[PDB]
Amino acid sequence: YATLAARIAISNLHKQTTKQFSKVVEDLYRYVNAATGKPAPMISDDVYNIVMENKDKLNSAIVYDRDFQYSYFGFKTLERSYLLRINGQVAERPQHLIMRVALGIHGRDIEAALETYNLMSLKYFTHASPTLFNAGTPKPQMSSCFLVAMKEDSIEGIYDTLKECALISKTAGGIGLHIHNIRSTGSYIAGTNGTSNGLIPMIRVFNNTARYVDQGGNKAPGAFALYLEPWHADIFDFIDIRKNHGKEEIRARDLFPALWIPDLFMKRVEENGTWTLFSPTSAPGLSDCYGDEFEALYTRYEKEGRGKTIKAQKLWYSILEAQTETGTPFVVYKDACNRKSNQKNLGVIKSSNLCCEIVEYSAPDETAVCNLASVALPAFIETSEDGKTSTYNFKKLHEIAKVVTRNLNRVIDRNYYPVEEARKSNMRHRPIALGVQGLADTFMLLRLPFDSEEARLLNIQIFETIYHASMEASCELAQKDGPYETFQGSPASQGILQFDMWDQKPYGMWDWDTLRKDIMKHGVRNSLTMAPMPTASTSQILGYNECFEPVTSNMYSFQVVNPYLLRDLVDLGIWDEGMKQYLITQNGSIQGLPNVPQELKDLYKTVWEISQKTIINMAADRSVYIDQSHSLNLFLRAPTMGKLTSMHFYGWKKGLKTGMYYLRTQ
Amino acid sequence: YATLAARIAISNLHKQTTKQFSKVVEDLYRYVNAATGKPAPMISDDVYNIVMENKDKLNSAIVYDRDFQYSYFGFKTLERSYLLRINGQVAERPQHLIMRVALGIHGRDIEAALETYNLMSLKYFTHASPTLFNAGTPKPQMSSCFLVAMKEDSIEGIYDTLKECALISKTAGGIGLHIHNIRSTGSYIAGTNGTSNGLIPMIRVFNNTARYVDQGGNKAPGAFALYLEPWHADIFDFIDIRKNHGKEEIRARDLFPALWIPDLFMKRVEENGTWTLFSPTSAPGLSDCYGDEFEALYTRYEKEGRGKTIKAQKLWYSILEAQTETGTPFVVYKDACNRKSNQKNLGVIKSSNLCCEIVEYSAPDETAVCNLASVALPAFIETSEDGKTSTYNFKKLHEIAKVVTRNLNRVIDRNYYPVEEARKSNMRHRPIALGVQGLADTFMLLRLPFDSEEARLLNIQIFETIYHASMEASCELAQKDGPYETFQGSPASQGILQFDMWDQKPYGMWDWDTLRKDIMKHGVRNSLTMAPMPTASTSQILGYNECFEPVTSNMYSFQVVNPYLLRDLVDLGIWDEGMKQYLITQNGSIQGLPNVPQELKDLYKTVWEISQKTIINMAADRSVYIDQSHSLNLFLRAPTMGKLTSMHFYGWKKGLKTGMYYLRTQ
Ligand SMILES: Nc1ncnc2c1ncn2[C@@H]1O[C@H](COP(=O)(O)OP(=O)(O)NP(=O)(O)O)[C@@H](O)[C@H]1O
Ligand SMILES: Nc1ncnc2c1ncn2[C@@H]1O[C@H](COP(=O)(O)OP(=O)(O)NP(=O)(O)O)[C@@H](O)[C@H]1O
Ligand SMILES: Nc1ccn([C@@H]2O[C@H](COP(=O)(O)OP(=O)(O)O)[C@@H](O)[C@H]2O)c(=O)n1
Ligand SMILES: Nc1ccn([C@@H]2O[C@H](COP(=O)(O)OP(=O)(O)O)[C@@H](O)[C@H]2O)c(=O)n1
Ligand SMILES: [Mg+2]
Ligand SMILES: [Mg+2]
């Protein structure tokens, strides 16, 4: 169909752009801001000198054919926010952006540079947007998220923290900020008859700084996620922070509430029992432990009159309300996250990030950071048997995941850190996050319904391979540069890998025993490797479905129909106008369509037609090979208090870390 | 009349309170917060030990009769916000508050303590509210205002500054904050295609922190004043910040805009000429000079295309609009303030304070502070000739002003400083601010219309004496403790006193030559002594008219009629119900009342009936004995663009520093 608008706008772009890469780096580097007279380079000194000392090798390495791998919407995304502009006009071709990104990561290892270039240009993998924006640029802030500790229960602590979010928000990246330690409404303050205002008014300050620190282009999200434990006395308002009605002095519409849930809360809800709310000042230490230690300390404070008791299910019901209307708060299980983190030698983890996938340690003086990349799952499909059936090439997937791991690991050293808390932190533990995109495609291309036994297996299979790969790559790194600073004492140091903490045998596609031997011997370079993220933008750049979720509709959206569906409907000579209309009219749903094979109706279920138990199951299956966590969106058809209840508890009992990211509805 | 409700509620208070002072200090000191279990003392260790080591001397010094010096509204003010409360109930009697304040200032100089006590209990003078609140208490923040420098044109500078206002707003005191150095809307920012948002959105952040840092009781005002020079490119919005209509993202209703006006602006308005707006980044140095140096540098930048030119009177007209509707921006003349400051050896002064009276030097690392007290002008009236006419006792006024000066000077050393910038600053230059209240009364009691030749003279006379006194006291201090750190190089070091900088001979009631001799010889302890403030609350505590303004109505307000008026109307046997009604119905105006002597109509003009030229004149007369500045409110009857125009220019040409504080209307 109109894949023809892609080619047009692509070679239009070729016409408005200098072909030779090294000339473009000259242009971008030499740039002066006409309106102001200021020399405003867009390449670093470092990457400039590199390109100049290697210009023939580099220019000739670039294959411009590989520009036509982009769908129309992929390309318009690139154009509109990614390709570097000279004075309003676009100056970078897609190949130049990639080549720049390759250099920004690799520096003088031109061999590494050429390997990344090739693999990216061919669509094997892609790095997260901040890397695509800033690698090879003079303030190269390439990380996607910062996990910030509230420094202290004081105006000074609060305003130091506010300063840090502000300094972070100048640049690319999202912020997860935990606040369990701020005293609740009405608590005593020494030196006044004044009472405390609590969380909400302090939230309104943060929300306001989110709105003010724009102007980083549109590279900042302008939103923070905030993490709270449900025992905090300010909980009812906190969860209603994105509510669309009620008083305005109580809402904070540019921020996301995220719950940090102890298992105790859930038991109490299930047991239909009491829940007690404390101010952190009448209940110290509560966020600084978990599991049993928490259970013991909580129960004691609860017996010692230190707080306020109400019915667990009163809170529970309010949460489901807030979630049904707004899609938030997110739900992340504190204990599951801490019980099963390779970072537990550092102390208690107090939050996740803005997309509920990063599970790293943060403290007033260490603000945890992470660099993300995603693998293009469908690129490892081949027909390779001999005949008609397609298989999945796991060798290449292991090979490619080792490359990404090495990339992400360099990005740590060549990263610009907005705040000293992020450099201190990331240099010590060197966490890393790999993800995937196009899981739904992979299945579709391989003729598998999402809810099949075969899909369940491949899910496990793929993730086993990425995790094995990354730990292998990381361990090779530890052999060249030493383990990361804080590796002694870690579960990985004691031979305990992620699935072990889930008390499971690995699916056994790869030799874990060899790997585990070498890790106890040599260490790893990275405390953490795996955390599948939303890929909202980058999967649009590679033309794939986000992430690891099924299609939302088969009507993608001018509106363009799912190419695999189209393919199949045409090959069955049943694609007419009745088809174009039935699918528009049902929004990319093909069930209940008179003349369509059952094989296709299974294959092209939309996420609303797939059962959430299956969804949670696959999240549980893959989770044992996930160092950190993943952004589990949930989708509900005709939503009810009961259906939502069984979904949290289902994931909760599965041992999940992120029980829910967004709740999406209608 | 109902002065009888005073006695009732006074001796009611006696019944609910322990008579003996040292028991009350015990009570207050020993206080424990029942709800929380926390020991919450309300007296310092230091003042406790003092009282205990001197309890008989102290308790017996206290005259409780002196509790009945308070009008009903004076007393209700004391009760409602000043007298220390034990668990909701009032624990301090007025005499205890005073005695505490005396100690908090004097420490172990019990002789000084007893002298202050006596003088205050008898209503000779009073210190500003923060002193009344906090002297003798464990965080004794006794200063009324902080003049804060915007630290830098950066997110870091801005958020360091935000932190400092927040830390200051926890406690008593107002903030004047100058921002001439923040780049305006649309300016370049290096490292993004992002433009700057300018002032307004950054103001909204400050306004929001004003709202959030309450809870210091109601001792913080919850408002800042912001100072800008009218060449700043963000000027039109900045002046409209308290506008009651229009868009909400453009207003900031809890802050006050104050203009810092160069003479150039005014000439240009008068000449009907061009005015040029710059961003500080395209015009550096502009706020860091004045007079000629400014004129030269401004003109050059204006010739070099560096900014945007429009008609002076376009801005002028908008200012008058904003002022007519909202009463702001305030108007303070930058050049007059800098030309005539004894602090010019330190560098350019960049703002005043929240009440337009403090004119002190502030810089990113020095935040200027000031401690205020006011003299009760009417307390120095006596009949003392022999017969019927009353005179004014200037000897006692010189004597009392020397006492206050010594008090204020101790408060500097025993002050708690919220931020290190304020301690650095105040310890070096030791500024001080004395004021007055009850000028209108004094005149009334002395049978003088405000606009008489006799009133004009006494105005000059009083102020000459306070200024002479304070410099004398201060110079005696310099003899015991040395001059203040930065006295060398000051105008006062070169024999140049305030009136000299106005190029005037002093009225000559006191020997200035002797004083001036001694100052060049020994120095002063205080860089600055005099800055008449609004006395909004404390004059209500002493039962006098604020400040140095005339009565606003003769219907004070249950509604209580002006006691002097009443006195006089009754003595003429013309006070009936027709009288009670004519004055209610005219809101304390007595002109155009059929049966009232002309002598009384002159004597009891309301500030709306008095001409503003006279008002400005007296402000000009007194200003030559004012180190710093004063809070000139203006009052306009039937306000018009022309009348307001001639008033600014009139004061501007008089050489005033504060041309206008509030513009008050109807
Ligand atoms: N003036 C204020 N306005 C609003 N909230 C305040 C204020 N002062 C303190 N708080 C809140 O109370 C907490 C303590 O503030 P902090 O700056 O530690 O004051 P403090 O004098 O140290 N009182 P305390 O912490 O009780 O010893 C912080 O969480 C503040 O948010
Ligand atoms: N991300 C942002 N959002 C809004 N305003 C900003 C942002 N970054 C900078 N500014 C404004 O631009 C000014 C410069 O900010 P600063 O923190 O100095 O950034 P910088 O990288 O140093 N850019 P420059 O000052 O041009 O070298 C400050 O007045 C900020 O208010
Ligand atoms: N323009 C953008 C988009 C995302 N991000 C960051 O990455 C997160 C979104 O993750 P994602 O994986 O869905 O987005 P992409 O990496 O595909 O653009 C946001 O929460 C931010 O933390 C950013 O900094 N700037
Ligand atoms: N309750 C109060 C009242 C005034 N003030 C400070 O003193 C200023 C008012 O000056 P003023 O002389 O009119 O008030 P008083 O000293 O008479 O209470 C305010 O701008 C604040 O700077 C305060 O800190 N707390
Ligand atoms: Mg504290
Ligand atoms: Mg800067």
Image (cartoon, coloured by chain):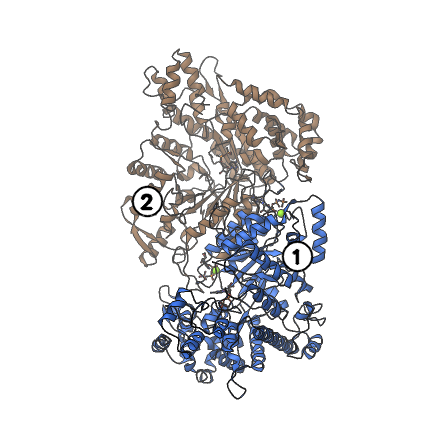
Chain colours: A brown, B blue
Tell whether B484 sits left or right of B570.
right
Residue closer to the observer: A627 or A131 = A131
Q: Quadrant of the C terminus of chain A?
A: top left
Residue drawn at (70%, 25%) of the image: A56
Chain letter of the residue beneath label 1 in the structure image:
B
- Residue placed furthest toward the front: B594
Residue occupied by mark 1:
B263
Residue occupied by mark 2:
A318
Quadrant housing residue A584 = top left
Using the image, tell me which numbered label, if any, was put on residue A218.
none
Tell whether A313 sits left or right of B139.
left
Residue closer to the observer: A527 or B477 = B477
Both marks 2 and 1 on one chain: no
Q: Is mark 1 within 8 Å of ligand 4?
A: no
Quadrant housing residue B42 = bottom left
Residue closer to the observer: B529 or A488 = B529
Q: Is residue A302 above or below residue A408?
A: below
Residue closer to the observer: B94 or A384 = B94
Task: Report, in whole angstroms, how far the alpha carbon at label 2 lies from the one at label 1.
Answer: 61 Å
Q: Position of residue B549 (x, y in %)?
A: 52, 68
Q: Position of residue B650 (x, y in %)?
A: 61, 61
Q: Count numbered badges in the picture.
A: 2
Q: Amino acid at mark 2?
A: Ser
Tell whether B42 sits left or right of B403.
left
Chain letter of the residue beneath label 2 in the structure image:
A
Q: Position of residue A58 (x, y in %)?
A: 67, 26
